[PDB]
Amino acid sequence: LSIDERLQALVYRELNNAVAFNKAESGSAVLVDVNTGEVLAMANSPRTITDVFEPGSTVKPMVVMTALQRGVVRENSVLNTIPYRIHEIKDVARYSELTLTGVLQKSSNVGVSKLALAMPSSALVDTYSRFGLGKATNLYPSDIERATFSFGYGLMVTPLQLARVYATIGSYGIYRPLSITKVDPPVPGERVFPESIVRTVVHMMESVALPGGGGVKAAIKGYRIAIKTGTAKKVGPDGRYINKYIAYTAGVAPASQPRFALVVVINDPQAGKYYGGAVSAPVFGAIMGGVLRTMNIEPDA
């Protein structure tokens, strides 16, 4: 088994605290070795199971990557983030303009939509699936659609598939499948994005774990981290959006060198702000914090 029981233990602990602390239905976390594909932790907090959900804001960095690749945008590009209609596209806050760094920091739906509007319908469908979305894990189907898909709506994924996305980010775009069994490093994978493109967006994602960043409460003293938090109002077995929320974070650390990819979900939180975009951001912080220390990984900041 790839599982590290130290990492499994503390992931389970923080997962229990976070579920109790938020009066949530359940939680799940998946820790993955960014260089090998090895699932080092995979836990639920009630024998509960990891289902599917709308990945929301975690798909955004891929959108930016694709855009950078297509030459749509340059590394220092500023986007018009003025909201528009198709059907309203808006943000947590009205910004006239954001940097690409800015769009992540602030999780700009408006800005990642304009990228996805300004690209083929294939461009995202390629990238997403290149990062392994719409593909089994073996341990996802017009502008309105191109747009929602740009901030991860009208498509669903498991924690496991997403953990595979963020592993591919940490490795700087070498795709590898997940592994429930030990391997010897290194593990050859598949080049799915240029290293230079993933590195850039990894650095930009560092803004999300800093002040002004939606992911600030995941911040860990002594380390850079590249994350994405959001939420998703659970949808019924019919299309109606239910009052349930599924808070999620995903990321890799330390950002200067990525060792680990972590994906944490907290299902149906009932305390504090249940809807809030960052509900799952503290426990991501607890878990990655414990991992890095436990693995004697040298401070990054």
Image: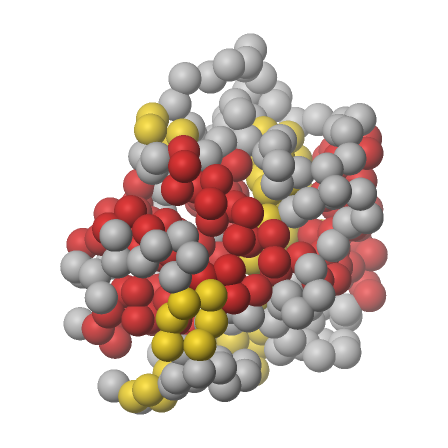
**Quarter of the figure with the N terminus:** top right
- Height in image: 133 above or below 300? below
Number of numbered discs overlaid on the protein picture? 0
One can see residue 263 in this view? no
Residue 159 placed where, x, y %? Answer: 52, 49
In screen coordinates, is 296 left or right of 191?
Answer: right
**Quarter of the figure with the C terminus:** top right
In screen coordinates, is 255 left or right of 116?
Answer: right
Residue 286 placed where, x, y %? Answer: 78, 50
The residue closer to the viewer here, 45 or 195, is: 195
Residue 65 placed where, x, y %? Answer: 37, 50
Residue 118 placed where, x, y %? Answer: 22, 66
State the colouring used for the structure image. Answer: secondary structure
The residue closer to the viewer here, 250 or 111, is: 111
Instruction: Examine the image and state in which quarter residue 291 appears.
Output: top right
Residue at 34% of width from left, 26% of height from top? 190
Residue at 39% of width from left, 61% of height from top? 77
Residue at 43% of width from left, 41% of height from top? 198
In screen coordinates, is 85 left or right of 233?
Answer: left
Q: Which residue is the extreme one toward the front?
A: 76
- Height in image: 48 above or below 275? above
One can see residue 206 in this view? yes
The residue closer to the viewer here, 218 or 22, is: 218
Residue at 74% of width from left, 62% of height from top? 217
Instruction: Examine the image and state in which quarter residue 188 appears.
Output: top left
